[PDB]
Amino acid sequence: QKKGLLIAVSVSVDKIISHFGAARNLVQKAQLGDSRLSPDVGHLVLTTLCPALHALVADGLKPFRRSSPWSVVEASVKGSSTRSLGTLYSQVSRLAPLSSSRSRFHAFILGLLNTKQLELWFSSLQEDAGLLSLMYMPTGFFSLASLSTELLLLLQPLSVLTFHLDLLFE
Amino acid sequence: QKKGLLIAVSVSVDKIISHFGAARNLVQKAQLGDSRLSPDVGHLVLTTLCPALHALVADGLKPFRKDLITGQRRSSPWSVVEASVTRSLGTLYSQVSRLAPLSSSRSRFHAFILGLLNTKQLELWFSSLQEDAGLLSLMYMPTGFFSLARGGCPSLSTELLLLLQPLSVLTFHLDLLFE
């Protein structure tokens, strides 16, 4: 049941990896990761990975005022995060055209891909015991996470792909 | 031999890996890559990997390039950066070049390497060199490392990539102005 959430992530990563497979060198692989040069990569990330990751973070989230995956990304910005992660959070939090918690979380995922910190950020969620207790019910994926080991392995391949996704791609 | 140049890289990577290995989790490893929290990473990179890669890029470099001020000026690894520069690479180049008032060409090249480590664009940048046949002919001898790196099984390029691969699991956050 929790592995179901992992499946959606895995299916998305394999599509993204397959997207880059069209390139025969690193320069061409970088072209395929740039949302201005290859909009299809932005489309893929926003419609497959972002929703899968959103559902994962939303799972077992204590509903309340309303808490969202964006709320999680907020309480994550630390003694439990890094300077670069906090810098990305701030950049995304100040993206004026974005008008919802969902759009902000999506843009945060775009930023993690660009900075190759996706695994890092999810790893950091597991280190904050206070956050997990504060934000999640006991039946939540991150309360039960092993699942965390598996999640991080699924996310790894994306860290060696060079992305240049416009944070305002939505 | 080009193998010696590669050995200095390999030895650099070993030390950097050991530095990060003090940490047990991903978040702690990230703190070991932040030069503000762990300045030893900055000192290590600048005194091990930076000179190693400087030597690799300088190998077989034709000593001069033409210019319209003084007819010609000395070529350097920094000159190779200038000639070669993705959107990610261009932003980094502009960054290093802006905050480069009276810095050595060596210092600016070192700074670019810091930036490549931060963005995990080391492999991509070296690939940019190899794919630019004009740049290689213009700037290097046929016996220069990056000119030669196009060929063999495994190539010099392949060896270089494999030596650098352990770094790809690490997260760096180095102040470009650390030196």
Image (cartoon, coloured by chain):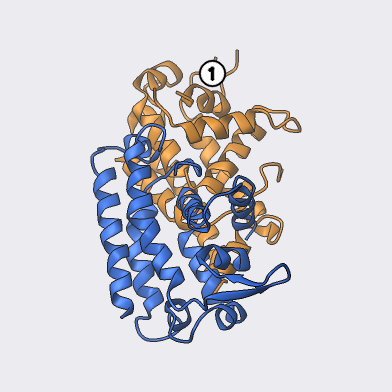
Chain colours: A orange, B blue
Q: Is residue A90 above or below residue B49?
A: above
Find the residue positioned furthest to the right. Answer: A97
Q: Position of residue B104 (x, y in %)?
A: 52, 54
Q: Position of residue B22 (x, y in %)?
A: 23, 40
Q: Is residue A100 above or below residue B178?
A: above
Taking depth in this image into account, of B119 and B82 the one nearest to the observer is B82
Q: Position of residue A129 (x, y in %)?
A: 34, 21
Q: Is residue B111 above or below residue B177?
A: below
Q: Quadrant of residue B166?
A: bottom left
| Residue A29 in view, yes or no | no
The residue under label 1 is A63
Indicate the chain on which mark 1 is placed. Answer: A
Which amino acid does the dot numbered 1 rest on? Pro
Report the residue at 38% width, 59% height from top.
B51
Q: Left or right: A101 with respect to B152?
A: right
Report the residue at 46% width, 54% height from top.
B110
Dot 1 alpha-carbon crowd within 10 angstroms: few under 14, some 14 to 19, many 20 or more: few
Q: Position of residue A96 (x, y in %)?
A: 74, 30
Image quadrant holding the N terminus of chain A, namely top left
Q: Left or right: B167 with respect to B177?
A: left
Find the residue positioned furthest to the front. Answer: B70
Q: Is residue A1 above or below residue A25?
A: above
